[PDB]
Image (cartoon, rainbow, N blue to C red):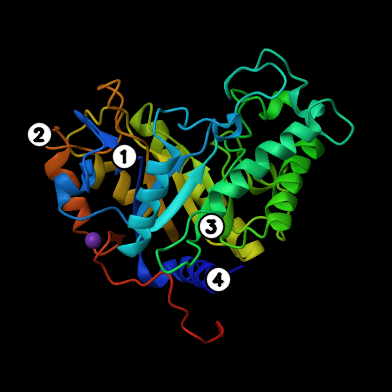
Amino acid sequence: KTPETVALLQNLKQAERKGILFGHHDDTAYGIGWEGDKGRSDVKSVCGAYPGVMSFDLGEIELGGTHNLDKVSFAHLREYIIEQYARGGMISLSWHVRNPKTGGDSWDVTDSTVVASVMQGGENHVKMLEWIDRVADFLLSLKTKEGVLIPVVFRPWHEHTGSWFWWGKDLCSSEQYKTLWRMTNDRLRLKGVNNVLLAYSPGMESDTVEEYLERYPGDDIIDVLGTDVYQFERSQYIKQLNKMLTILTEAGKKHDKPIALTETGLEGIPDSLWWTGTLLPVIEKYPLSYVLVWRNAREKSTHYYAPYPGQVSADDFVKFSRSPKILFVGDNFELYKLEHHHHH
Ligand SMILES: [K+]
């Protein structure tokens, strides 16, 4: 891993001391009522600072086209990534990859033999490695104008304990799933992709650490232990989020990995006090390195997870943002600076 990448990991590992970076998907790409405006951010428009983490998706890079599945160009993603690094924030990338057997999208679960087909000897193995190489080439293009590779937390194969993606629980064995991870790591390493940290991120199906780790590909592959948990009903969310963050904290101590709430949110945040009244009291109890809420879909204006100006939860988001526990660009962290000393 590059020096800046090791520094990022070491700074994620001191979350207990520094606080929780706040994140938003596609934050500088678009939001409610806009797309592509230079420097614009629904998060910054509400609270005045950029989120400490921004994530974007590489889905459809494997098809060799110019835009991802959410119609954002890869050349724009690279710009947004360079700009987030320049201001000192973190970047994460997910990968809603197409179905290599059916030609469908990530959510095509018609065929439960897709992962088998990309194993060694399978009809789609070479193509799967070509697809991963296309991700590798994009990652290698994430450079500062001075030529420094930009560290990224790459989070492929997510939500694998559910069965809504073609790599999900009912669609492959535990060993097949771990092999996806090994193929991914192998190709990234061969390509010299030394600017990636890998994050593991199943949802809330697991009730225990044993279950959470059943499909874990190993400490030598994974750098960040995450989970994706959304609010559908408040009491259940509080129970299930506490349950998963307890699992993450226990597992992260057992395996010496930082932890993160890699996706969460309340769609349309109709609860005007969601941020301080529901989310913060849960997450502040756990040593999270970051918490990321999902995109503000310009193309479906009910589908948003961060506020925007005038949105009913916006004032409360401002109050949340002022918590010393929650970190935005401008706050007291330096992700890419090594402080050169062991933990004790
Ligand atoms: K803050």
Q: Position of residue 220 (x, y in %)?
A: 72, 61
Residue 173 visible here: no
**Residue for badge 4:** 6
Q: Quadrant of residue 294?
A: top left
Write down which quadrant ligand 1 falls in: bottom left
- Determine contact: label 2, label 1, CB under 8 Å: no
Q: Amino acid at mark 1?
A: Ala
User: Does dot 3 land on a helix, a strand or a loop?
Assistant: helix
Mark positioned earlier in the residue sequence (3 or 4): 4
Find residue 99 and name its label.
none
Q: Amino acid at mark 4?
A: Val
Q: Which residue is at 56% across, 43% downward?
A: 201
Taking the view exactly as shown, the residue that stands out farthest to the top is 110
**Residue for badge 1:** 29
**Residue for badge 2:** 310
Against 228, is 289 above or below?
A: below
Foreground: 54 or 276?
Answer: 54
Q: Nearer the viewer, mark 3 or mark 2?
A: 2
Q: Position of residue 152 (x, y in %)?
A: 50, 56
**Residue for badge 3:** 249
Taking the view exactly as shown, the residue that stands out farthest to the right is 121
Dot 3 surroundings within 10 Å: few (below 14), some, or many (20 or more)?
many
- Determine contact: label 3, label 4, CB under 8 Å: no
Q: Amino acid at mark 2?
A: Gly
Against 198, is 124 above or below?
A: above
Q: Quadrant of residue 221?
A: bottom right
